[PDB]
Each structure stands twice: as C-alpha cells, then as structure tokens.
Amino acid sequence: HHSEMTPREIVSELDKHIIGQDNAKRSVAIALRNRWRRMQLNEELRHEVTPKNILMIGPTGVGKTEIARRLAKLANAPFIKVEATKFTEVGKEVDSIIRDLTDAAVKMVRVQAIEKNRYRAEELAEERILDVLIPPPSAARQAFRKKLREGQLDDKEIEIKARKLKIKDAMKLLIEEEAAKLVNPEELKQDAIDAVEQHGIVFIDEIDKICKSGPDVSREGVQRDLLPLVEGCTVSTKHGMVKTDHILFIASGAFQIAKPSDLIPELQGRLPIRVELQALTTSDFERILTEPNASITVQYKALMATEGVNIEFTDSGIKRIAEAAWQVNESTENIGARRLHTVLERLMEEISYDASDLSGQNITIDADYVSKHLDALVADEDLSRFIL
Amino acid sequence: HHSEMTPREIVSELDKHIIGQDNAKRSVAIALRNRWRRMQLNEELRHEVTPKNILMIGPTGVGKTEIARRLAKLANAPFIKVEATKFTEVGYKEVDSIIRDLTDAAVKMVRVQAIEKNRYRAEELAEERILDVLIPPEPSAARQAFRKKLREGQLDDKEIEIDLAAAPMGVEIMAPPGMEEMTSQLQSMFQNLGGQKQKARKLKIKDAMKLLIEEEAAKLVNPEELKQDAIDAVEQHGIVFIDEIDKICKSGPDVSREGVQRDLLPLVEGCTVSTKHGMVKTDHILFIASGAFQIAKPSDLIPELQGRLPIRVELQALTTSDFERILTEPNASITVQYKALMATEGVNIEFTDSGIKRIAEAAWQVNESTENIGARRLHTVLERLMEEISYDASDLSGQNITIDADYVSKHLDALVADEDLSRFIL
Amino acid sequence: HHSEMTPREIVSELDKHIIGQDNAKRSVAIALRNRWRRMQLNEELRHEVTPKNILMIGPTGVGKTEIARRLAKLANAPFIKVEATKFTEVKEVDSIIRDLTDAAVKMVRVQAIEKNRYKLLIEEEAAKLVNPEELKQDAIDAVEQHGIVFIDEIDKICKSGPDVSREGVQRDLLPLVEGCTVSTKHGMVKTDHILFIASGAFQIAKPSDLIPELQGRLPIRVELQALTTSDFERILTEPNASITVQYKALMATEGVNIEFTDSGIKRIAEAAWQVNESTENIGARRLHTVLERLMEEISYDASDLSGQNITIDADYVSKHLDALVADEDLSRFIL
Amino acid sequence: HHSEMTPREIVSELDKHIIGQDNAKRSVAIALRNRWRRMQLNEELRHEVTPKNILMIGPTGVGKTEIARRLAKLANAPFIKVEATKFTEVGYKEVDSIIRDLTDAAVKMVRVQAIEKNRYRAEELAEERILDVLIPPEPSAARQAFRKKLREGQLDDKEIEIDLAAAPMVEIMAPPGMEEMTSQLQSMFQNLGGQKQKARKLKIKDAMKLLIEEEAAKLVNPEELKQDAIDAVEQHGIVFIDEIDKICKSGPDVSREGVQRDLLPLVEGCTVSTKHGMVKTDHILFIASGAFQIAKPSDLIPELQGRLPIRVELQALTTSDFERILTEPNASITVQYKALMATEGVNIEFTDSGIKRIAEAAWQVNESTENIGARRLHTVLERLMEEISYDASDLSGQNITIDADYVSKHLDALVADEDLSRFIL
Ligand SMILES: Nc1ncnc2c1ncn2[C@@H]1O[C@H](COP(=O)(O)OP(=O)(O)O)[C@@H](O)[C@H]1O
Ligand SMILES: Nc1ncnc2c1ncn2[C@@H]1O[C@H](COP(=O)(O)OP(=O)(O)O)[C@@H](O)[C@H]1O
Ligand SMILES: Nc1ncnc2c1ncn2[C@@H]1O[C@H](COP(=O)(O)OP(=O)(O)O)[C@@H](O)[C@H]1O
Ligand SMILES: Nc1ncnc2c1ncn2[C@@H]1O[C@H](COP(=O)(O)OP(=O)(O)O)[C@@H](O)[C@H]1O
C-alpha cells in the first residue's frame, strides 16, 4: 500500500539522487508522509483531507523535476510531466493529463506483474521437473532441487503431450507455459485505477507562463480548466473511471516574469505548499558528477569497462569539467545542470569511439586531459552554442 | 425522497460549516424548502412550479461554493461545480456536459448507498467462499476455526487458489481525444455479451478478499433498478453550481461571452439532455450562480437569464473576526484536520486563543498587502506555519506542542512584513 | 390521432395561460388548424401543401415564447427553442433536429410508461410486450408530423465582415425550412412538415433585411404589443396556475393562508413597471424577481407562521419594495 | 428508366408548373434529351460524352429552382438542392456530402418501387404463417377454408397468438460528428443478438400488417436494392447548386475559391464513398444558379467554367406573370387555399379583378422595398386570407367571394405604408 517511511527517511533516500535542494526535498517528503497519515484516520476525515499540492519556484536545471521523478519512483507511484503551455493553443483538452497518467499506470502495473510472475513461473517450472526425477519434499526432491539450480545437470535428457527434451531447453519451455496462467486482467486494470487515484502524482512544469489583454484571457483560461483537477473531479478514460480527488500535483516555474500571486485565487488555495529552489554552483557541479548513485561519471566508468578500459576521474579533472560547464552557461545561455551532459560527451567522444581498441588499459582523466579537449571549444562562444 | 427540514433547521445546519453569510443561507433554504412544498401540491401545480434559482454576489473566498456544496450534501442531492469560462472557447467542451457529469455523479451516489446495504452481506458470502477452499465440504469445527482466524488474524498473506470470473476479451481500442468516452462504452458491450464463466487463478487472501467482495456485492444490487433510480435523483433533487457567471457578461469577446449564456439558457428554462445512463430532464434541477460582479452587473446578463434567477443575495466580505471563527468553529476546520494529522505521528497540537487570533491577523494582512484571495489564505499561512512541525512530527511523538501568539509571530511576521517575499511563499 | 380543434378553440385555451396578444394567438391558431386540414386532402395536395411558418415581432418578455410553448403542449407536440446566434461561431445547424428528436424520445417514453401501468403479472407483460425500438419509431413520427421548432432572436443574424457570417446562418438554416433529411442516432428524420416559429425585436434590422429565400418560407407575420401596467395585474391573477396562485399554494403547504388584495396586486405591478422604466426593461419577467423579494420574509418564516392568515396589502408591498425600488443602483443587483 | 420525351414535350410539360422563362426550359430540355441520345451510341462514345451542365443567371424568385425540381420529378430522377455557401465554413462539412444525401434519396425512391412488387408475395406469405396458427400442419380442406374466410371475411377481429421478432438491446453517447456512425453500430447489435421471434398475443387485423412488414424485408435483397440505387444516381442523377455566384472571388477569396476547388472533382467526375456503396459522379448532371450582380461567370476558376458549358439568363417576372402564377400552375397557392378552406366547409372564389389587384399588390411591395420575386405572393395572400382562415370554422356552409374590393380593403392600407410593409409583408 502506501509506504510507512518517515519524512527524514524519505529525504535521506532522495539525497542518494538529488544534490542539495533540501527545502524542496522536505516539501515532497511531508506530502508523501500525509499519504500514510490520512490512511490512519477515520472514514470522515479521509474524505475531508485532500493532498497538499506543492508549487516549486526556481530557475531551470536545479532539479525540480528529478525530485518529483524520484519521489514517485520511491513511492511506487504513477508519474507524468505536462507542459503548462501545451493547453495554451487550445483545441488539447486539460483532461488529457489524467488520460495519459492512467496509461502510464497500466503499463506500470503490467511490468510489476511480470516481475512477480517470473519468479512464480520458474518455481512451478522446476517443481514440475522434480516430479519426473522423483515420482511422488523429504530428501531426494530437495537434492534434485539444489542440484538443478547450482549445477549444469540441465544437459541430461529428461522426458517431460509427453515428449522427450533436454532440461536446458525444457526449462525455458516450462516457464512459458506457467507464466501465461498467472495474469489476471481484471485485477490488473483495477489496481491501475487505484494507483492513479490513491498514489497518483502529477507534475505541471512551467506553470508560471500561464499567469496573467489578448493573451491574458487565453492564459487565465487554462487555470480555470486546470481548476477542477486540483479541486477533484471525475475524468472518463478507456481504462475506467478515474477520480482526481486524491492525486498529488506538483507545479514549478521560473517566476521571473510573473509571481505566484498572479495565479487565480482558486488555484492558490489549491497549492498551499510553496518552496523556493536555489541555483546550482560550481561546487555543486563537482558533487553531481560523482556523489549521486549511478552518476554520469560512474556510468561512463562502467560503460568503458564493458570494453575493458578502466576510467579514473581525478579531482583536478572533475574540477575543470565542472568549471567548463559553468563557463559555457555564463558565456552563452544558462541551461542549468544539463550542461554537464553535453560537456562530458564531448570530452569522452574520442575514448568512447576507440574503446574497442583500448581494451586492457587504464585511462586517467586529469585536469590536463580535460583542458585539451575543452578549452579550445569553450574559448569560442560561437562554437559553444552548436557543439556544447 | 425530499427532506422535510424547515428553512430555520437548514440555516442552523449550514452554520455548522459556514460562518456568517446569513443572507445566503436563507436563500438556499427557501429553494430547498420549495422542493418539499412542491411535492405536496396537486398534479397541475407540480409542473408549473419551477425551482427558484439563486444568483450569488460577493468577493472571492467568502464561501459561495461551500454553501452550495453543503446544501446538496445536506439534501442528499447530486452536485457539480462548473466554471462559466470553460464554455467560452466552445470548440471541442459542450454545455450539455454539465448535466452529463451531474448524472454520473448521481450514479456513484446511489451506488455507494447500495454498497453499504449490501456490504455486510457481500463480505459474509465473500469469506464464505474462502472457507470452501480451506476446508472442502452444521459448520462443525474447522469451518468455525478458520472463520475466526480469518477475521482476527493477519494470515491473509498466505497463498490460496480460488476460482474467479475474468473477461477473456482483453481488447484495446485507439481513439482520438473526443472518442475517449465512447470507446469505453463499446468495451463494456463485448464483455457483457460473450463471457460468462469463472477461471481458477492463484492469489493472496489479502488481495483475494477484496476481489470477492466486488463480485458478491454486484449480484445483490440490480443494475436496472439502480440506474433508473439515479435519474429520479437528478430530475427532482439535482443541484448545479455555475461559478464566475459574471465573466461571461458583455465587441469581439462579448459575442463569445454572451454565447455561453445562450447555451446555458435551455438548462435553466428546462430541456431534455441525453446521457449514457438515460434521458435526463433539467426542468426541476436547481441552479446556483455566483460572481464578483466588479466588471459587470446582473443587469448585463441576457434578459432570459435574469428571469430564471429570481433569488438574489450578495455575500459580505469576511473580516478578521470571521477568520478567528473559521479556524475552529466549523466541523473539520483546517486546524482540526492538522490537529488530527499530527496525532497520527503521536503529537498533540494545541492552539491558544491568542495564537489563533494572530494567525487570522497574518492572513488578513497578506490579503491587504498583496492580493485578496479570501479565506483561502488561511491554508497557505497555516501550512507555512506548521511546516517545521509537520516534518519533525515523527521525532516529536509523545510530546505536546502548544502554538501560542509568540510561536505565530516568530514564523510569520518576518514573512508578512516583506511584501516581495509574501507573494511567492504565501 | 391528431386532435381537431377550430382556431377559436385554440385561442380560447391559450387565453387560460397567456394574457392579451390576441394577434399572435390568431396566427398560431391558423398554423395548428392547417395540420388537420392537410390530413383531409388527397395524396397530391399533401406534399404540395407545406406548413405556414410564423415570424413574431415584438419586445422581449411579451409572451412570444409562452404562446409557442402552450401551443405545442396543447397539441402534444415535440418542442425545442434554439438561439439563432448560437451558430454565429464558425456547432452544426442540424443539431436543432437532433435535440428535437432526443426531447421527443423521452416524451414518448414517459407517456408510454404510464400506458403500461394502467399486478406483478401485468408489469411482467409490460416489460415484454413493449418494444424499446417501437418507442423510438413512434418518436420519429411525432417529430415529422407534429414537430414544432422555435428560433429566438432571429433578427440578430441579419446583415460586412460579420454580415457574411450572420447571413451564412440563414443560408445554413434554409434547407431546414425548405425541407431536408437530417440523420440522427434514433433514425432518419424529415423536416418537411415541421412547423417553425421565429421571433425577434427587429429594432436594429427589419425582416426585409433577411435573405429573399427565407422571407417566402415565413408567410405568417404577427407583431406583439408591449405589455402595460393593466396587463401586469392580469398576469398575476387571471392565468391558470399563475405565479401568485403558485405562491399561495406553496405557503399553504406550510399551513399559512396567503391572500392578495386588489390594492396590493396593483402596486406590485406598478413596482415591476417602475424597475423596467428606471433601469432595463426585461418585460413580464420582472414580476418573478419582484414577487420573490416581497415574499422572501414570509417564505422563510412560513414554518413558524403555520395556522395564521397573512394578508398582503398595498402597505405591505410598499414596505418591502419602495425602499429598494427607489434606489436604482440596488435595483440592478437585487431586482 | 430514361424517358424518351423530345425537348418540345419536356418544355410543354414544364409549362404545367413553371410560368414563362422559356429560354431556361429549353436549356434543361436539351440536357435531359441528351441523356436518351447518349444511350443510342456505341460503347466508346458513351464514356467520352459527358452531361452538359447548366449555369442559370437571373434575379431571385424567378423560378430557377422550380425548373430543376419539376425536371427531376418529370424524369423520375434523384434530386438534391444545396447552397454553395454551406461549405464556406468547411468545418466538421465535406463537399462529398452532396452525393451522400443524393444516394439516400435514391435508396428511398427505389425502395418504394420494390415494395409495390413485393406486396403480392409478402401478403401471400403473411397470411400463410397465419394459417399455421389456425390449423397446425396438400392444403386439403381446413387450410383452403380458412384462406377463403380470411380474404373475404372480416374474421380478423378474433384474438390469435403469433410469434414475432423483437430485440432486447442501448444508447451510445457521441459527439455531433458521430451521430450517423452510432446509428449504424446500434443496428449491428440488434442483428447480432439473435435470429428468432417472440410469441405474443395479437389481433389478425393488426397482426397481418405487422407480418407484411417482416416478410417484405426478407423478399427484397439488401444487396439488390442497395446496388440499384447506385445505378440511379450515376446515370440519372441531377444536382442543383444554388447561389454559386457567392463563392466567386483577398481574405475571403481564398476560402470562397476553395469551395470551387472542392466542388471541382464532382463536376469533372470522381468516386465518392457512401454508406450504400461506391458512386461515380462522372455522368451526374449539375445545374448552378446565381444572380451574378456582384460577380460574373468569368470570375469562376477556369476549370469550373469549362464544366458549365450551357449558359442561360432568366428575365425578371412582371405583374402579368404574377396573375398567371396564382391560377395556371397545378396546385397553385390560390387553389390550395381553396381546398384548405373547403376542409372547414367554405367555398372560396377568386374574381379576375381580385387576382389582378393581388399581383399589383405583390409588385408594389417588391418595388417599394425589396424584390423577393414570386415569393411575395405567399405573404400578400396570407395577409389577405388571415381573417378568413380564422373564421373558416364558423363560416361553414357559406360562399365567400374575393373581389377587387375585398383585396383593396385588407391590402392597400398596408401596402401604402412602406415601413410596415417590410415587417408585415
Ligand atoms: N541536484 C541535482 N543532483 C543531481 N542531478 C541534477 C540535480 N539538479 C539537476 N540535475 C540534472 O538535471 C537533469 C534534470 O533536470 P530537471 O530536474 O528536469 O530540471 P528542472 O529542475 O528545471 O525541472 C537530470 O538529468 C539531472 O542529472
Ligand atoms: N463563511 C465561511 N465559513 C467557513 N469557511 C469558509 C467561509 N468562506 C470561505 N471559507 C473557506 O473557503 C473555502 C471556500 O471558498 P469558495 O467558497 O470556493 O470561494 P468563493 O466563495 O469565492 O467561490 C473553503 O475551503 C472554506 O473552508
Ligand atoms: N401575455 C402574457 N401572459 C402571461 N404571462 C406572460 C405574458 N407575457 C409574458 N409573460 C411571462 O413571460 C415569461 C416568458 O416570456 P417570453 O415569452 O420568453 O418572452 P419573449 O416573448 O420575449 O420570448 C413567462 O414566464 C410568462 O409568465
Ligand atoms: N415561373 C414561375 N411559375 C410558377 N411559380 C413560380 C415561378 N417563379 C417562381 N415561382 C414561385 O416561387 C417559388 C420558387 O422560387 P425559386 O425558383 O426557388 O427562386 P429562384 O428561381 O430565384 O431560385 C415557388 O414557390 C413558386 O411557386
């Protein structure tokens, strides 16, 4: 059901992925904790209590989206990201948010079912093999069970319409037959509805652009159409009837042009929690390259390891990589932490291409190797917009 | 099924939720009371007498919508709130959708009332079928043993194989956004025709119990009697609330603005609207409209609409004395909810009289310093005030936290004093 | 089948609801009587003879719509009212016949449920012998032969930029009056024999500003006089189930006997006449808002006033009204 | 089939309905005569020869549409009238809809022709199933006895229980564009539910007519009836496009000429899909009309001018023509008002001097304000007859004579005032 984690355990889990932005983490943790707190109340208070929506404020590239993505992934919750300006053009309907979110939940519950159906099909597949070895666990059945998993015993011929086969090729055929009987289409579609209603999470990006003569009537019309979603309503979908009352909504935006006070008063009352996010620094970039679990540099260490090349990133090399991304954002356009992705690939493109010929070597990326493939490019701002 | 409550008993019940706004409570009581007065007349007068619709006037956040919500909830009536500007575009949402979503809201209303009557019986037969798998076949011993262990025990995590019904079709249809409602109706037809059977599958008693209650409760209630009864709820008891009707009043946009009034005209004057649950007649449906009317006036409405809104009430703006009452008096007020939410973690929150008073002063000052959003400022102010407690409530378990006037001025006055920061955070 | 009533019998029944406007009652009586006259002709003349459509002219709130509603209710005919300006935006015009069919399906369905009730074995034969598709077929026969359509504010689509879009509504409405075949979910519907009644103020434009093809499809023209103070008094009392009789019976449910004096009925009408002259003239609709504001105190206290006789005089009217009617700024919001 | 009448026999028949406009009648007579002329040619010349489409020019109300209506009714051809401005919005209407409604008019036309032939076979099979209920089962005696008693006798008032078909089935919500589709889906569930007949008690009087309808559907093949209507549209189809002058030619000109480009594949010929099957528009005859006061036929796109070879100007009607329209045409408005008042028992008689002043009154209104053509005769007559039509119930058994004095009493007062003539007349 809903996870029992405390807000401190949720923020501690988010620190494995997002760097900094502790205030934003505490806001989503409190909202996720209220999901469990509402389950502990009586029947009257469960309907009266609605989720507390979060309005994030900050420049682009500070992690507003990754916090929401990891939260839904931490809460095992369906997630969708919608641009607020998509509805500005008009006839797309605003209800499409719930329609596409539901579709994401239907595929989610299917993959989670196949994951739980595989271990169940394999247990019953080898269980039917043990009936041929020892006709009816006692001893011999437990002996052939441990010898079938650990050993290469599968090469022996075993007759399992009865037909003779090899346990290696009979095991994969018995998994196909057992996995087809473990799926319930009715309970799968109903759980996808409960996933959207109870656990649903919706992230509305760049909601500041729809704030307030000609365009303002079109802008404030999106909020009036977004209003029944946050206040709760019924949306018809192909999969069934989806109620948005218990869905959590997380909005974000720059708010340089407008302010959250420019939103309609009915929407402000539906976005009670507000959190400002600080912009990232050069000291933060050095942290993002290494600290987060499966960071882009750790991934590249493992990717070249597939070819047999050991990549090592020195601190002086990581420092100039971070200094490179900061310089490009200042010289041209500030895209946030996304600059680290394009800068890392441009430096690593020569190693990634020749990695097949570098098998068996240890390549050390220092401050000098970084400045050779970068400083020439970072010096030209005209080249920095196309290449970086 | 019309409630016999007098106008004074209705206003007294509304006082349990809404604070003040006595004129608007007396308006909705008259409309609801006429529902019972009409049912006592002869056949000729029942059709000639039509509900008296209400046009509410007042600034935002004064409780216009909540009065309509509690009115329909008090009368056990289907209710829907629609924004008048939703139909300004006109290219598809249809104006008929107001009765459509009102019909579907009534079907769920009469369904939950049918589930509660069938609940204890469906749960009795659901667990009865579980006992047939545990002990294959007066109850003797083992059956009464597993029955008591199933209700009291957490043994539902065990694996049990029970036969259950399933729809073998499993077909998905691609549809453009307009056909999203229609294709779902086609999917229910193919499952209703061919498949009648039950297939043996392996489940867990925790998930198998909830799946058995749905199957047994469906057999107890008849769909033909329930679907036609919901239509009788929309025609007699239906209640519709049209928000921000002042924004559709009156060259370029005014033709599209007044077009919404023309489209809403057959609803209030009465007409026949087709729904998937049946044919619905809007003649006796009660309509309530609300608006600020700062830009326009009720005279700027089309003359055909003015006659269909005979009852007029303006609602007064809330004051600081009202904010102090809203924080406590109403049932399930925002402080009552937060008090119970922190109690989940084991923390006892207490709000002093002077603390509640300085919370209201903060919300009042923000509405004046920046933008007046009405009583909705109380949530943003309270959530900002309690965000430290709500995060630490896990570690504060077993402690009594008292919110005094000093605690309020510490976490708020700093923010309210700076107007530039007040707009972002509050 | 279809009831045969002389034009005087139609007007005499309309007098039980509408007050005055005798010129419009005589026009609608001719059209409904032609429904029975065409049934008595031969096969060749039935298709050649087309219904005579009516174009009504007059200010708002004079009873143009009530005359049409009571006419169809008297003939048990499907009725629909659509605003001509709804098609100014570039909804299809065929939706007029679609919503007319939907309203006729429920009409013949509710009327058929009563016939089946006229005890458990009789109801089991009612759910069997009655066919759901046969009711759909009976509705289509009611739309083609007896159908009545009312098009409000038709003068607003008269005639350079918007005039091409305004007159385009007339051109799209043309096949409906000339006759055509419109497809609906309930079946195929033919508009040849449907009666159409149009109305408008015609202060901005004139019927001559309509396209020439449309003028010939509206042979009957009638102007409705503006209601006066003497007419307002008659609307409060004379019509069957009048707004005052309704409010007299609603209070009677609580146990209170309400009586309206002749002096009060006169000043109630004078109050409504004063508001239409001071701010905006909404016609007889002003009586609805004025009555409710006068009776709002009695309607709320009717539970505690049970067993009492409350008499509404001219003094009680002047107490709850003259204060509000004198202030025009408040008259727009409250009245 | 294809009528063999000569151009002179066509025009002579059109004079029974339309008055004057001889140059236009000769144009439509040539186009209908070429339908028969092409039939007598060889296989190569039949396809190469295409119908000669007609463009009518003249003021409104001169009878352009009545010539097209009476022409198709004379040739027993499917006919449809469409306004050229209907497709200006082009939202969803597709121009292909002209052939769609034309096919539906042909299906109903050939269906009634199939009902008359199936009447004797259905009535034989309808009473055949009734005889199985009376005498349970060459005919021997009892079957031949009840057969002669059912046709000759009024014995149908007896209660007889016969089995008849019905379906248990549902409503579907759809946007206005799917209104035609959902009607087809509903018919498919009624056919799929089951094939059988439910037993119910009835009367032979009402059971015989209900048995004829069920048998008549089985006798006619839905593939033969549906495909025969396609042959009626391709060869005999006649389409009238009104006010084509309003789609002639910057901002509106792109949307106006866009209608001609969408109308172009219809006149040049193409394949249009209908619910009844595939229809080819190559040989369908098209007739266009317009006032052409604002624009000219040369303003049309060059590809459309080549597809409208026949050009005819229609003259404006005069006072002498209005006198003829009130009397000469079959089922004229004055004869129709004579029979309508006859239903109440009143005999109406129009004098020659009264008819003459009516025509002069209709001309004066067209001259004083706006000229709407012969349509003015409808409003002028109804205003004159409105007092008689209301009292027709109490005037039963009386003979009312409409003279020149009765015309000037109810009209000249109203016609003299031009401000009131616009509203009332
Ligand atoms: N605090 C952070 N820690 C780690 N990665 C981050 C952080 N902030 C941004 N990123 C990077 O930015 C990308 C996504 O940024 P996103 O959250 O979509 O920007 P925004 O906050 O403007 O929505 C991710 O690929 C991630 O690597
Ligand atoms: N008089 C009142 N008494 C209690 N709560 C109120 C009152 N007025 C407003 N509220 C609060 O404001 C919210 C309702 O605002 P709403 O009525 O929707 O705004 P509006 O009246 O502008 O439509 C509710 O959450 C309610 O708690
Ligand atoms: N002559 C009349 N007699 C009785 N009621 C009238 C009369 N004229 C107007 N009304 C009132 O006006 C309302 C309907 O007006 P309506 O006919 O819609 O206006 P319009 O004539 O502008 O269409 C009804 O509620 C009716 O009580
Ligand atoms: N020459 C005519 N003979 C008889 N009736 C006519 C004649 N011209 C017009 N009408 C009358 O006018 C109407 C037809 O006008 P129509 O042909 O549609 O106008 P247009 O010729 O401008 O398209 C019919 O009702 C018909 O009675």
Image (spheres, coloured by chain):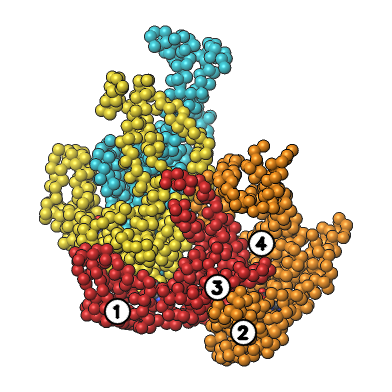
Chain colours: A cyan, B yellow, C red, D orange
Pointers 1 and 3 within a single chain: yes
| Circles 1 and 4: CB atoms closer than 8 Å | no
**Secondary element at tag 3:** helix
Which of the two marks, 1 or 3, is nearer to us in this view?
3
Q: Quadrant of the N terminus of chain A?
A: top left
Which of the two marks, 2 or 4, is nearer to us in this view?
2
Residue at position x 32%, y 41% in the image = B117
Image quarter for ligand 4 equals bottom right
Q: Is mark 2 within 8 Å of ligand 4?
A: no
D333 to the left or right of D3: left
Residue at the disc numbered 4: D98
Q: Residue C283 sits in which quadrant?
A: bottom left
| Position of C82 relative to B189 (above/below) | below
| Chain ID, mark 1 | C
Gap in Å between the C-alphas at discs 1 and 2? 47 Å
**Secondary element at tag 1:** helix
| Circles 4 and 3: CB atoms closer than 8 Å | no
Residue C33, numbered circle: 3
Which of the two marks, 1 or 4, is nearer to us in this view?
1
D125 to the left or right of B307: right
Residue C265, numbered circle: 1
